[PDB]
Image (cartoon, rainbow, N blue to C red):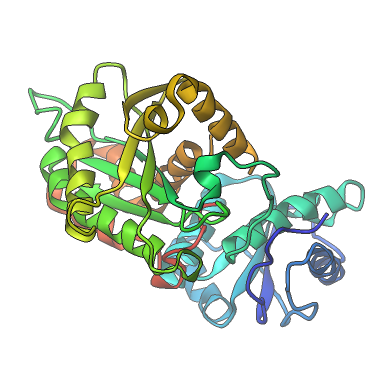
Length: 368
């Protein structure tokens, strides 16, 4: 089963074998079969890999980085075989590849990759990921809701973490938080570029950054050849992570920042229609799109729309994945929170900068 839209050519790739208790055999043959399968599904990966590297996992993260630096810096892609399902090592590999060196990776447990029985299905899944990471689309929806069809609607999802420890009367709103955001860039809905960021003073920082951040999403959509310099006319927005209470906060302290970004980018009086929905069922907080166009059938048109979306819920799920990966990226912060439970706001900010995805991967689905 092929892919709807093939990713970019993958010319230079290799493998990194992290040794476990039992030694692996047949790895390069497996890498070859892997690449063959990807090609068969229409992913243009070079059948030929540059010779891979095998090593055991070093004691420190700096040693690891030092060992993988040249391999990771010189390839577009690395398939990493872990010796066992070990999230310390997974997390280290992702910090190395996503952050420090900036190269796409897939992490596969060696036993699963090398196991002949069931191998093709696993290769199918990894291949789906590879196709997305490199810009392609996997599935086509047979019947898109009129509203998505026209190619005039941008979909956005974000979630906000708040992983501080609140104590001693510390204000909740001022509490440090992390935002994860994804959005679509075309009518096809395959690609969902992400943004992450830190709010060291919470809502004060959200207020300072959100307008400009959303502004980048609008700019990303408009500069896509597919859309022909069109700003989306509609914007559907999913917010995760909020209790029924915080609904007011989202409406009052977040949605206006999006409105401001639109006011900054859009022709005067031509601002797009916006619908805000929160996931955590789904609850529509604001709708300018569905009632307008579909009257009584609005609700069902949106439930059909979000059903069409599940075809690949994605905006909210992807945003969560983005947050989780951010949590993996910012090791200094979480290590500190395991110990002291308290961290300086300046530490929050600079650890946000240090744990930012490498620019090589900036608009990519690295989190997938």
